Amino acid sequence: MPLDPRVEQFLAQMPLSLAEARQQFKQGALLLDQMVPPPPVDTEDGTVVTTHGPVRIRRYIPDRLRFSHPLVFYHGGGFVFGDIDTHHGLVARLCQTVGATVISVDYSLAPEAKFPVPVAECIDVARWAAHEAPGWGLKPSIVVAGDSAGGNLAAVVSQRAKDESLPIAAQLLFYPALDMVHETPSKRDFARGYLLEADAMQWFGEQYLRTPDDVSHPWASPALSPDLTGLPPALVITAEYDPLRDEGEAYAEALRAAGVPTEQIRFDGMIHGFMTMPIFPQMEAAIEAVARFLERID
Ligand SMILES: COC(=O)c1ccccc1C(=O)OC
């Protein structure tokens, strides 16, 4: 299907120390939010005590509460970039459109923290949210969610949830990274020129992983896990022109065949990252998909 016209324009108009690279990523996110301002939303900043230290969070409170579980959201950025501010545009809209309380998580970034530290942190935050939920008037079971590297974390938390005695009602994976071992067709076909590139992915792995062997660890590559039975209901959103497309869709098929209630949606014409790029109407369409999916959980 042709590249979406606005996407095509965005790519055509695209033109460092670690600190500078992080600031650049932050500046781009700011520019997009200036172009398409987020909805106003009540928020509260907090800090959760994890097994690897304090992790800042931001709780988003909907104008009108309509969903009975808290959402715990883990931002993307290759494990190296991003924060609660870079993903505010997405989270504010998830909050208000779903009518859900959302916990956005500022997990520890690489290379300063290495695999599997943020996985541990993300579990600890999920556990905290489950314990708080009754006092917010909610069910203790949580929904985990994330984009890209954040979708990785969400998928891994979900695979660990039973073992960690963590009640999870659903998982929302937005163009996740799931298999660091295998090349897929999309990974070859869209390797360069679609925002998320091959070289960047390599560099992200070099920052996050301890050694090259970690690629086969199931907490890095959750698509490798042989037993997906009994995992939480899954919404897997992919972009057509994304190197990570094929691994995301393959995992959705594997979940489905393992009896996990699964919705798999490819947004045609789109690229990696589109759900934090509000210049594209498909971002809000995908958020509507989330709301529709979550309507069916209870
Ligand atoms: C070396 O750290 C890890 O990879 C790890 C961490 C906790 C539990 C298990 C493991 C493991 O699989 O290898 C020891």
Image (spheres, rainbow, N blue to C red):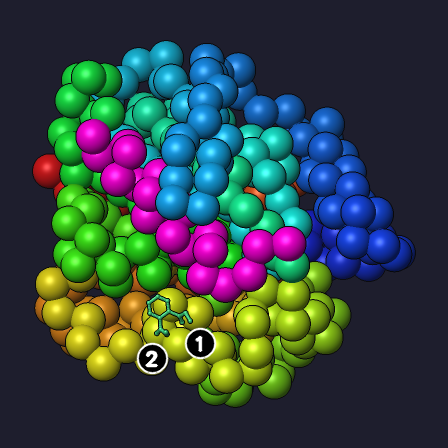
**Label 1 with label 2: CB-CB less than 8 Å:** yes
Write the residue at 53% across / 15% down.
Answer: 40
Q: Quadrant of the N terminus?
A: bottom right
The verdict on residue 21 being magenta is: no
Report the Cα–Cα distance between label 1 and label 2.
7 Å
Q: Write the start and end of the magenta stretch as one range.
A: 112-131
In the image, is the residue at mark 2 within 8 Å of ligand 1 by its beta carbon? Answer: no
Q: Residue at x 76, y 58 (%)?
A: 11
In this rendered view, identify the residue nearer to me: 169 or 297.
169
Place of residue 230 in the rendered image (x, y in percent of width and height, measured from the top left): 11, 63
The residue beneath circle 2 is: 224
Q: Residue at x 72, y 33 (%)?
A: 30
Residue 53 as seen in the image, left or right of residue 289? right
Mark 2 crowdedness (10 Å alpha carbons): few <14, some 14-19, many ≥20: some
Can residue 285 be seen in this snapshot?
no
Residue 200 image offset from top left, x and y in percent: 70, 69
Element marked by disc 2:
helix
* Ligand 1 quarter of the rendering: bottom left
Above or below: residue 189 compared with residue 294: below
Label 1 secondary element: loop
Split into 4 quadrants, where in the image is the C terminus? top left
Q: In terms of secondary structure, what is the magenta stretch mainly?
A: helix
- Residue 120: in magenta span: yes
> Mark 1 vs mark 2: which is more N-terminal?
1
Q: Going 67% across and 31% down the picture, which residue do you hit?
A: 33
Residue that badge 1 annotates: 179
Q: Above or below — where is 207 with respect to 292? A: below
Q: Amino acid at mark 2?
A: Leu
Three-letter residue code for mark 1: Asp
Quadrant for residue 202, please give it. bottom right
Residue 163 vs residue 263, the one in the foreground:
163
